[PDB]
Length: 99
Length: 99
Ligand SMILES: CCN[C@H]1CO[C@@H]2OCC[C@H](OC(=O)N[C@@H](Cc3ccccc3)[C@H](O)CN(CC(C)C)S(=O)(=O)c3ccc(OC)cc3)[C@@H]21
Ligand SMILES: [Cl-]
Ligand SMILES: [Cl-]
Ligand SMILES: [Cl-]
Ligand code: NA
Image (cartoon, rainbow over all chains, first blue to last red; front, side):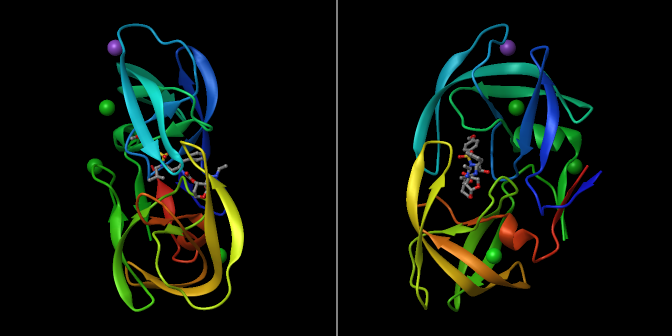
């Protein structure tokens, strides 16, 4: 699809067996999801943005379905105010910015 | 252009006659730039990001060139970690996300 940017580019995702709304975010290096449980190993990480840093759990090799497209990669889990799909998974679904 | 997301989608912008680097950010509603001098009056605005809220200065109807495309609109100035081009100006340059 082609998503215009008049409105937030929100899509439905499936992660950890749950459906969630997430923002397709080209200004995010990494994917960050609100608190939830994921299977396997994780390690702590700090990530920063406007407002400063938050502590997150880093899970690697997680499958996510993004608007119907399956991708695998690292997912950060922590107290983010919005679920964000960052470049590490946007690349896997072939997303590009065009103008 | 068609911009992939394997690296940060950084572009050159021109504002106040200065060249700067900025991030095309579909996750940002608004454009936020690091501290600089802009003409005219400003208005207060509180913006929230991943680590919390910051106060910024809101300047309206500012001329800004973005990867060679002319835009005129609102620019927020404040302690952002990186210059961010948000949806308010990505729509002015015709940008869309595609996959
Ligand atoms: C209330 C919403 N206002 C937000 C919405 O737009 C507003 O205007 C612009 C400034 C602020 O927007 C954001 O902070 N946008 C966030 C994504 C984001 C969206 C919503 C809430 C929080 C974050 C960005 O798209 C991605 N951010 C990075 C950029 C600030 C460089 S980030 O979420 O902090 C980030 C993500 C992954 C990551 O891995 C290393 C590291 C950092 C305001
Ligand atoms: Cl990854
Ligand atoms: Cl590619
Ligand atoms: Cl505007
Ligand atoms: Na894992």
